Amino acid sequence: EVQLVESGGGLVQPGGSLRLSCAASGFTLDYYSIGWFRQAPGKEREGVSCISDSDGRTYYADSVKGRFTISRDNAKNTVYLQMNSLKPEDTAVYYCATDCTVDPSLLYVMDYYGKGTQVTVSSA
Amino acid sequence: VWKEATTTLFCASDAKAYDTEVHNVWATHACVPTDPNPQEVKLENVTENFNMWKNNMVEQMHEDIISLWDQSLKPCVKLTGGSVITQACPKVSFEPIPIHYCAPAGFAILKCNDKKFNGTGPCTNVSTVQCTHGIRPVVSTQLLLNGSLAEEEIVIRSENFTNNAKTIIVQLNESVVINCTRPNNGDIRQAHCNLSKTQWENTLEQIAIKLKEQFGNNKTIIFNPSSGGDPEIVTHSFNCGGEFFYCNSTQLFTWNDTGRNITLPCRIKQIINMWQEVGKAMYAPPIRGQIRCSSNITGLLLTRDGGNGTEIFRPGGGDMRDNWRSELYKYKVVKIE
Amino acid sequence: XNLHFCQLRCKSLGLLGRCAXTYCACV
Ligand SMILES: *[C@@H]1O[C@H](CO)[C@@H](O)[C@H](O)[C@H]1NC(C)=O
Ligand SMILES: *[C@@H]1O[C@H](CO)[C@@H](O)[C@H](O)[C@H]1NC(C)=O
Ligand SMILES: *[C@@H]1O[C@H](CO)[C@@H](O)[C@H](O)[C@H]1NC(C)=O
Ligand SMILES: *[C@@H]1O[C@H](CO)[C@@H](O)[C@H](O)[C@H]1NC(C)=O
Ligand SMILES: *[C@@H]1O[C@H](CO)[C@@H](O)[C@H](O)[C@H]1NC(C)=O
Ligand SMILES: *[C@@H]1O[C@H](CO)[C@@H](O)[C@H](O)[C@H]1NC(C)=O
Ligand SMILES: *[C@@H]1O[C@H](CO)[C@@H](O)[C@H](O)[C@H]1NC(C)=O
Ligand SMILES: *[C@@H]1O[C@H](CO)[C@@H](O)[C@H](O)[C@H]1NC(C)=O
View 1 (cartoon, rainbow over the protein chains, first blue to last red):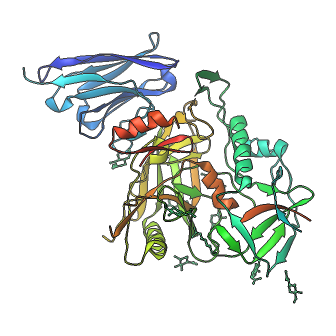
View 2 (view 1 turned 45 degrees about the horizontal axis):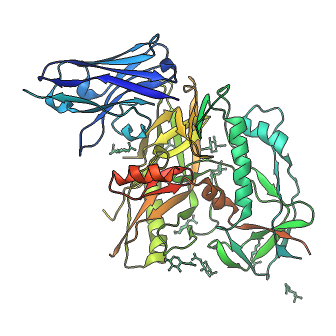
View 3 (view 1 turned 60 degrees about the horizontal axis):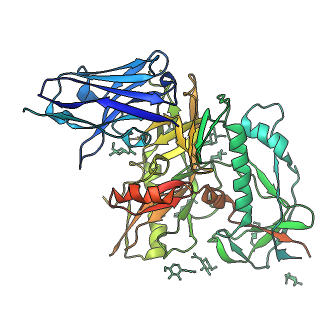
């Protein structure tokens, strides 16, 4: 079977950082667009980040540009999302997804994704 | 003659044995050559009943096109019923050709020549033929592409209009051209479609008029996007040059009484929900180089909300038997004598 | 489409789920 194993995330102070990982069994990640989108309860989907193809072309939602970094370990068939300078509005459930896109008008084409990793940004 | 009947039809096309385009390749081994001088026997004053919703021709066509896709567009991975099916998944030339469906010896096909025929019940101007017209087996959702136009006015068909669970098939009388491109510039999965805003607006208006004609002239007609579901039926999805396009159709189906080109954003997806059977199909990445389709929007698939003065319609589709239905509606197979 | 899983999916959206051929549609 094909599947996506997510890890990382949790709770940090605003301006802190996290790292998410998504490990895929069943594919060769560089043959696909793999990445993350996010959703908070009662709110619409938001784009986050995608990595793609042999040269690992990367794509970012405007709201996370310069702050998030997506990368890929081919040997581990794993994709990583380094989340720096986190802000409160980054609080959401992040889902690792195939056919990943960050285009605001196409976020709901993503229907093959790996269930929640919760990320919460709050001053506590 | 004659009698409504069921038999195994055979297909005819002008497929070229030298073309490696996969519809041609399939049709080359699956079909016989077309008649250059096809004959039609007009029975101008004969009435015959049709039921596009109960037409075995559709089932046969469905089978054939499943066979075509299963031979022609091979996914690298197919996930179905606990099975993982893998195979060589070459990127191929993919551009539908017209297919004719033909009655064997002993049988004939009845064609309805009534230009406003609503697809069910009596048809008064009937003729007899060996084969249907050429039907392009286009697989899509929401919009019917490269099909046949209504000869006179727009025609809307439903198995039962008062039943909101039954799909509405709209047949336009003027094509609305839509140009979809994955620009070569980059993001190889980013694509878009352009079409004329005013043509589409007027198309919506005329469809709305035709819908009021059906559901009441005091009724306010509203178009809204899909309520939700699989990406395939929420977006206008289709295959352009072997690549699976998913195009956001919000701008197409958001309309009420209240730019030059409508530009729909699209994604090319590799992991698809299958139309032939329940499961997933996984294809290789988009080809680099030219991905480009220009198509005639010739029809629509709509659903009605139902349940106080206002009627909301949304883009539908998913059951490709309806797509085949949009073309085979005027036909039925009969046995001579 | 699996109708049951589809109806679950659409339920989460406050919608009914039904099949559209081999696809899940939420009405
Ligand atoms: C289509 O675009 C609109 C506006 O950009 C957006 O609200 C909607 O979610 C999009 N549809 C899909 C399926 O992504
Ligand atoms: C019947 O159909 C034929 C062919 O489509 C057409 O030429 C004719 O005008 C139609 N009406 C008749 C025969 O009254
Ligand atoms: C598209 O429509 C135009 C005008 O109706 C026609 O000339 C053209 O042949 C059509 N193309 C296809 C593929 O149906
Ligand atoms: C197409 O059909 C519509 C019916 O809604 C009609 O108003 C329009 O004039 C027709 N156009 C042509 C070119 O036949
Ligand atoms: C189609 O028209 C016929 C009349 O020719 C009628 O008997 C039938 O009920 C109609 N079906 C619809 C409107 O679905
Ligand atoms: C169509 O559906 C409505 C809704 O219940 C029903 O009243 C009507 O009888 C149906 N038509 C036919 C021909 O069964
Ligand atoms: C669509 O493509 C045709 C040629 O294929 C072109 O003439 C037309 O202007 C295009 N329309 C749009 C809206 O891009
Ligand atoms: C419609 O027909 C044209 C001309 O054959 C073709 O280029 C285009 O790809 C077709 N569209 C679809 C969706 O098959």
